[PDB]
Image: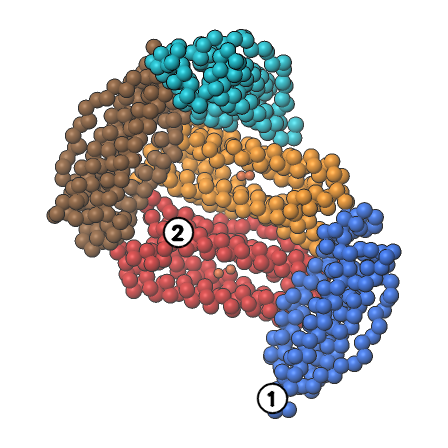
Chain colours: A blue, B orange, C red, D cyan, E brown
Amino acid sequence: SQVRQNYHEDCEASINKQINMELYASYVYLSMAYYFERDDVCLPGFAKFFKESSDEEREHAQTFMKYQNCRGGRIVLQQIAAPSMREWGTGLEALQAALDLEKQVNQSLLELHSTASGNNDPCLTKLLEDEYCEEQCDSIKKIGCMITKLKRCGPTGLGECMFDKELN
Amino acid sequence: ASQVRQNYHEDCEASINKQINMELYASYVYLSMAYYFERDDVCLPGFAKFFKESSDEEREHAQTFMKYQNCRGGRIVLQQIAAPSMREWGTGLEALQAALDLEKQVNQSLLELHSTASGNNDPCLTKLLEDEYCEEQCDSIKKIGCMITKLKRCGPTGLGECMFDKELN
Amino acid sequence: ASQVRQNYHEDCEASINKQINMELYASYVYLSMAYYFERDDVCLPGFAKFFKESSDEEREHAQTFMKYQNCRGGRIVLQQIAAPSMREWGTGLEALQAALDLEKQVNQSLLELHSTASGNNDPCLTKLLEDEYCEEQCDSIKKIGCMITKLKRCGPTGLGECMFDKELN
Amino acid sequence: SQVRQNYHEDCEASINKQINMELYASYVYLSMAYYFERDDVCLPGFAKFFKESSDEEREHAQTFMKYQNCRGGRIVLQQIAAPSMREWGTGLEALQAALDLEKQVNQSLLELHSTASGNNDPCLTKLLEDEYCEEQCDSIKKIGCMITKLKRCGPTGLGECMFDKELN
Amino acid sequence: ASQVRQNYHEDCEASINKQINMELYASYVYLSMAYYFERDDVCLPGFAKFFKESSDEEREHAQTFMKYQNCRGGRIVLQQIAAPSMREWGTGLEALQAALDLEKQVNQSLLELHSTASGNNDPCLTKLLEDEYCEEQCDSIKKIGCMITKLKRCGPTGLGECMFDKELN
Ligand SMILES: [Fe+3]
Ligand SMILES: [Fe+3]
Ligand SMILES: [Fe+3]
Ligand SMILES: [Fe+3]
Ligand SMILES: [Fe+3]
Ligand SMILES: [Fe+3]
Ligand SMILES: [Fe+3]
Ligand SMILES: [Fe+3]
């Protein structure tokens, strides 16, 4: 490829798995979002929050797809796994699953940060610092704080309603 | 002496410096509380905002006594600012109680500053205390006392703590 | 530990807390310089404003590390803020060379933290550390260096100190 | 009380009597105001002036009530005496009674200023200087000047009419 | 007496009248300084404007005490305004040190009035006196002190006097 320069083969394949990981995480958040719009659940604040996180994750994937093209590597998209669950239980259990999801996505980010370093691609490591750090710490903290807040407000009943309203 | 020094006693100057350190101390305390309420296991952003503002407020009060020192020709002597002895503030209610006690300590020290300036017939010092550390310091004490009262009523824990923090924000 | 914690070494936590203390101390020193230049026998409002803004900036840097400590689910442990090395900062030039030293000292501590953060596989700490030490410390250490050169040229005392203080303001 | 600090018991009770004194003075001015709206009197300038002074005094009372609460003392409101008169006579006699009223309210203010001083409440004395002085001297002078002016303009007849119009 | 009079000692009345005279004299002196610096062999318009505004301010202070005298139903008794101590005020620095002296002198008389007002149980006189002596006399005596320090630093004559006069303007 005419633009390819100092782009290791294994950085190329790791970028493709991060793309799949973000598309998957976007799919989970989509599952959670419409689970909370069910008639027997009906937590619209939760639903909006997970709709947006699913748009966010789909945007992160496209960011890694654009970086792939811009390095002259070639995107390899695979199947996107079905979400592990269909019914996410309570609002609290959804958030705990989402925190796990976010940590799973960001562990995978670190694994790609070491592959970028152990191949001397200074500018893929530059980009990953602007994902895995730049805003990852703000996002992991945000779900952590939501969990702390929901456990305080009382994780069921009226405390779950009040938490929903201040999400929305 | 000084150019701009006119009816300014020595132990007024040393009490002013003691007051500067006290305000800087209280500012540090509030800074401790502000970022405690931003820990991921706490997450009381309304509490955090209130104490961050009280921290800035206390710092500006320290600077008011610093300008007045310079202005009567005294000399600012700045000392070490001790860290709060206890930085696990616990609940929102425990922090408000510690804060109320802090406010009264600062105001006790000011009140003793007011007697020393009385036994020196430095009416300017007594006036500075009156124009700056009384109209709103009786308000700062009352607003905390009133937050305590509200937090107690709403229930000091759980859902009522949440709704208190919301109405604070 | 804390549930948001992920890849955060214990020695990084302690070094962030040391850096919070350095920035607060930095801020205290600049507070001293600011009100010393507001003394009725000094009256350099340019220097005074400069150090008072540097003192605010330093306090802001300290909160940046406090926020970050909370990010990674570490524990802010605040320490006593030492009294500044002196009270009389001498000429405007002496105050500036002391400030340059103080800046290099704070930046030195960032470097030790930077190595510690690199030898612990913490990409995001070194990213944060790298920005503060490099991005704008080649702003602030350069600008104080130029002020020192400019004040030596304009003449470090007398009329030249006056004109420097005006062009600062 | 959790906020109470350096607030002597006798400053607390004196604040309550000043509250009653201001509510009383507000009641007198209300009497004077509607006396001057009587069909056989009909001095609308006088009436407006006394309506406003009755609002003013009711506001001063509330100021002392807020200060009581803010020091953590407790408000004790008593009966409010009927005004000493029903018919205030001429405009001039109303003003002379009002000057007496104002001096009676401000003497009571001084008595509370000495109690605040002889108990070392620097910040109750601070507040009373912002009532008994801040504007008391301006207000006592204003009624004094009105009396001087009405005696000049001729205190009865057309001079009373002219004075009314420049009040209004 | 007068029918608005209430709690107003006879010796307070006489001391207010003395203070009216001091402020008018103060104002006259500053009038001298202003037009001396407008002489064709002096031509310092900065100093000239400064003293001409101080002369207006002093005249305003005098009317403040006149108004107050009327408040308490005392009698304004005006006295002859003495000629200023000289006509040639010398250097800008000498004029400023004379102004500092003049300000301290007027402020001295306020203090004697303050004690007289306190030893006569006149809370409102000392309140008024306290404000003028303290509130802005730590404005005006400090600002002249800083001008004196600044003019000594910039060099009290020659080019430095020029630059000071420009930064005044
Ligand atoms: Fe993500
Ligand atoms: Fe304070
Ligand atoms: Fe306060
Ligand atoms: Fe810094
Ligand atoms: Fe800096
Ligand atoms: Fe009244
Ligand atoms: Fe004056
Ligand atoms: Fe003056």
Q: Position of residue A111 (x, y in %)?
A: 72, 75
> What is the quadrant of residue A143 in the picture?
bottom right
As helix, strand or loop, the secondary structure at mark 2 comes to helix
Q: State which chain disc 2 sits on.
A: C
Evaluate if marks 2 and 1 touch, with contact meaning CB atoms under 8 Å apart: no
Among the 4 quarters of the image, the one containing residue A146: bottom right
The crowding category of the residue bearing disc 2, from other C-alpha atoms within 10 Å (few below 14, some 14 to 19, many at least 20), is: many
For the residue pair C133 and E144, the one nearer the viewer reads as E144
Task: Note whether A78 is above or below B157 in the view shown.
Answer: below
| In the rendered image, residues at marks 2 and 1 fall on the same chain | no
Residue under label 1: A3
Image coordinates of residue B145 in percent, x first then y, are 64, 34
Q: Secondary structure at mark 1?
A: loop
User: The disc labelled 2 sits on which kind of residue?
Assistant: Ala
In this view, the residue in front, D75 or B140, is: D75
Tell me which residue sits at (63%, 13%) in the image. Answer: D79
- The answer, for residue E77, to whether it is visible in the render is yes
Q: Is residue C168 left or right of residue A25?
A: left
Which mark is drawn over residue D88? none
Looking at this rendering, what residue extends furthest in the bottom direction? A2
Which amino acid type is marked by label 1?
Val
Q: Is mark 2 within 8 Å of ligand 5?
A: no
Horizontal side of residue E5 vs B166, given as left or right: left
Residue B166 x/y as whole percent: 69, 46
Question: Which residue: 74% across, 36% down?
Answer: B153
- The residue pinned by badge 2 equals C48
Question: Is D16 left, or right, of D141 in this rendering?
Answer: right
